[PDB]
Image (cartoon, rainbow, N blue to C red):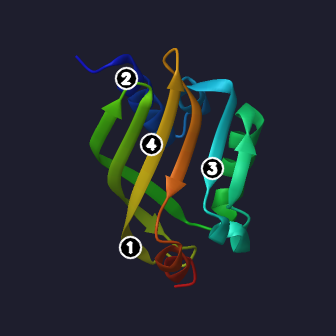
Amino acid sequence: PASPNIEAILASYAGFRDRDIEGILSGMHPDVEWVHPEGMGKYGLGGTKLGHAGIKEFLAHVPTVLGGMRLAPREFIEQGDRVVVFGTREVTSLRGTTATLDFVHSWTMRDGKATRMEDIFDTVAFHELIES
């Protein structure tokens, strides 16, 4: 009996897992905001992206920096229209080097879709992986 917010979030994670843009966007409002750490600007993966168009820009740039990424959500903290997801993710460099890193995804929802999704993580360790 997963709540509608968590149901919509799970569908988007499935969309990223299966590389299905339709599924990713199924849980996003057209005016959604994607926020990543400023420290990722070194790789063009930091700051804010706006709308469906911004998400597509972001996902299209990732393969230029990383070899792969696989998310494993573990914990969902929900209060009202805020959902905080904790998990790990397997990240592969362009050289095929792999590491297990932590992620926090802070979701803001309205009417069952996301108005905001922010990714917070140890950017120093992420850079280490990218360059290895």
Percent x, y of residue 60: 71, 50
User: Would you call the spot at circle 2 few (<14 residues within 10 Å), some (14-19), or many (20 or more)?
Assistant: some
User: What amino acid type should be assigned to the residue bearing mark 1?
Assistant: Ala
Residue 7, located in which quarter of the rendered image?
Answer: top left
Tell me the mark number nearer the camera, choosing from 3 and 4.
3
Tell me the mark number nearer the camera, choosing from 2 and 4.
2
> Mark 2 vs mark 4: which is more N-terminal?
2
The residue drawn where x is 49% and y is 78% is: 129
User: What amino acid type should be assigned to the residue bearing mark 4?
Assistant: Arg
Gap in Å between the C-alphas at discs 3 and 1?
23 Å
User: What amino acid type should be assigned to the residue bearing mark 2?
Assistant: Glu
Tell me the mark number nearer the camera, choosing from 3 and 2.
3
Residue 67, located in which quarter of the rendered image?
Answer: bottom right
Residue at numbered disc 1: 99
Tell me the mark number nearer the camera, choosing from 3 and 1.
3
> CB atoms at circles 1 and 2 under 8 Å apart?
no
From what the image shows, is residue 51 above or below residue 69?
above
User: Would you call the spot at circle 1 few (<14 residues within 10 Å), some (14-19), or many (20 or more)?
Assistant: some
Gap in Å between the C-alphas at discs 1 and 2?
28 Å
Residue at numbered disc 4: 17
Percent x, y of residue 19: 54, 40
The tag on residue 35 is 3
